[PDB]
Image (cartoon, rainbow over all chains, first blue to last red; front, top):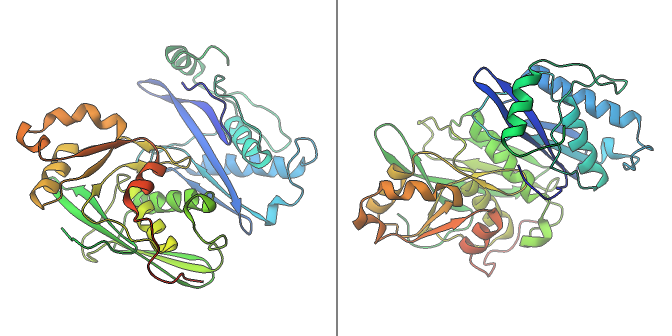
Length: 146
Length: 193
């Protein structure tokens, strides 16, 4: 784990058949024309979850202090380190929503809380699989808030 | 190895199962509309490394003296010789960042320092694999200064003791230290507008 709250970074949990692991999602909002780069050997379901999170934040732009016109003024890059490790599944929707909101609104997300959950387009958290391995992996690394 | 420092060129390391090899990375920055050509028959992970390094440099333009609007004024082209050999892997991340910053800020990059490391989007240098072969190849080709991530310090005793006394390793953990150590402080060429 890490200690300081970071801007545009969020802690999430991944399931593998040999146990759980941490995955960090980090995003960057640079001035541009409105694009979405998605890197880190991502599968298709995870890219669609990123787009669902971005559409939810575009619909509710007054509630979180986001800029009112980021959809055609800001390029967004979503990187899931590291490369050469393929990553897929819908269970990182909450992590991407937190990371994108932190990068657009310039407020630091805190990194001593691991999270997991699938997001829908109404902003509605949906249940996941592999809870036990994820929580054990979060408890190995010294994170005590889920 | 090369001797004279060049503008937009960096000296990286690679390894095949045969052994270590020197990579050279060349970047050109010409007037344009904002594009990114990536040639030299590169893998997909290596293209994602280049995009991550460029997105890092687009957010810290005033730190390094880059022009403040190159994202829609400059076309970049990254070429990794030679064109026939395929190249893939995440381990050439900070050498691409050094080459791109040298090409945009018009500051020559030192070519007597090899480097290797994986860059992230916050500018962190993540550990790599195959340290022994890369450092042996860099010692055979004549280079005596190495930049290496902080977390690969454990692998350094896989080397013979007479190689470690001839080398001079700088252990970094963020890419700002690499760009401060590699780039010569004065711009030579006129800037790409």
